Amino acid sequence: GLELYLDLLSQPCRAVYIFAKKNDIPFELRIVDLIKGQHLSDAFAQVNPLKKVPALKDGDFTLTESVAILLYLTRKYKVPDYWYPQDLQARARVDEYLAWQHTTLRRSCLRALWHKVMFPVFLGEPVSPQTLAATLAELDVTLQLLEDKFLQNKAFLTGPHISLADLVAITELMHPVGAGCQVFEGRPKLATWRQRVEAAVGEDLFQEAHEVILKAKDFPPADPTIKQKLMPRVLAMIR
Amino acid sequence: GLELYLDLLSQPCRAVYIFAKKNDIPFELRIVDLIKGQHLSDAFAQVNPLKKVPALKDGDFTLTESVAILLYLTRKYKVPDYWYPQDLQARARVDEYLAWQHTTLRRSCLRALWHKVMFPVFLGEPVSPQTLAATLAELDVTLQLLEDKFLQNKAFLTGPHISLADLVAITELMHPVGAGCQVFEGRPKLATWRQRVEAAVGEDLFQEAHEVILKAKDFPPADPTIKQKLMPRVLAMIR
């Protein structure tokens, strides 16, 4: 049957996890622990040769990329049209955001988690104060774009209802939130939007999906072995 | 009516250009000249507040992000099935590649062009032999992934027929090819793939869309004023 290789630490996994639970899509949970390097192992490379999460598997069908996984689940499980509307322009707005976040907001949030908490606390590697400040400055810029280019004065990023776009954006914004960054303080429109999204998702589910990312400042250091294999993996993931 | 703001210099514009020409879609072409910093004008910041190309405009509907544009044109004008296959699994592969390429092949092909030609020539900015070597090294890593994860032993990247994925891939690879880099050498399966893609697209149209990028090594160095405006944009674009 349907299997989902996830790790709620990972941003795209929370987006997929929330989408699957919210829509009651029956899947088998295969928790892949990234804090142990369980993704660089022989047992996981058989599943996904690229050694990454999220990963979907259903028989001989395998799929990577959360954007592909979400669209696939949307179509196969005939979820509500609001996730990805029939209307061509309304649907184009979801694609516009999904294509936009790869190199911008996803990149920012991920760098905020690693340059402010993961390297120093988890990897034990000090980060240049100049690199940390640049990372947070750039986080502010992408937050500003999120409001100016997408949210504007609407209830959600693509219209009056929640869509795949809102789902991917809030799991992205929870990265810096888990790192101690003041993401919504000083941004009333994004704070209003956050409450509308977790209300549409269901507080229990939203809270459940974000338990590991909020304990990020509490993970113990990684022993010399795991750290040696994750270092080049992380450095390549956050540029 | 349908308008397409493009510059054959940028990779995403070539994808949108070839898809619209090949499918006989009626549109007015608005050439945005990146070399003359026309995208940074106060009049183009009206069409797209981000000042980037490609940009689609059909009435009060404006759309950015090449992936969203390609998918939109695929629905608005109903084109051959192979671009974005109706088959659930074949379609997912297209989405998977379109999502994967943003932070990988798009970035490597773009950095290759700039460290090998655009910086030294067009911007009078020398690039250390190791910066170029690093960029060309990462390029192969992605060229390898392009074969191991997507192409493999198939005619095209997501099937026996060309899709939006192949169109985006070959327009991306034409950047390092326009830079005089080694791309299809030593890689016979990509070399074979290239000719199938050019033929599927049509050799004349493929040529036509790549006249600007194949003359990249001949662009006159931008004068101190234009260089000053573009310098931030460039480093922030090739991140």
Image (tube, coloured by chain):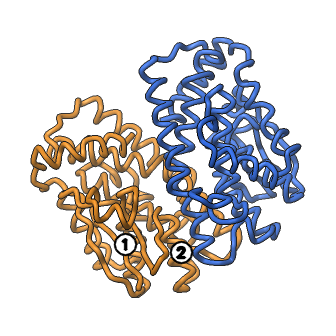
Chain colours: A blue, B orange
- Quadrant in the picture for the C terminus of chain B: top left
Report x, y in % for residue A182: 62, 31
| Cα gap from disc 2 to disc 1, whole angstroms | 23 Å
In the figure, residue B112 lies in which quadrant?
top left
On screen, residue B16 versus residue B97, left or right, reads left
Q: Amino acid at mark 2?
A: Tyr
User: Residue visible at 28% across and 66% down?
Assistant: B8
Q: Which mark is residue A104?
A: none
Q: Amino acid at mark 1?
A: Glu
The secondary element bearing badge 2 is classed as helix
**Residue A70 seen from this side:** yes
Q: Which residue is mark 1?
A: B198
Tell which of B73 and B217 is nearer to you.
Answer: B73
User: Residue visible at 41% across and 43% down?
Assistant: B140
The secondary element bearing badge 1 is classed as helix
Q: Which residue is mark 2?
A: B72
- Quadrant in the picture for the N terminus of chain B: bottom left
Report x, y in % for residue A27: 87, 53
The chain holding disc 2 is B
Q: Answer yes or no: are tags 2 and 1 on the same subunit.
A: yes
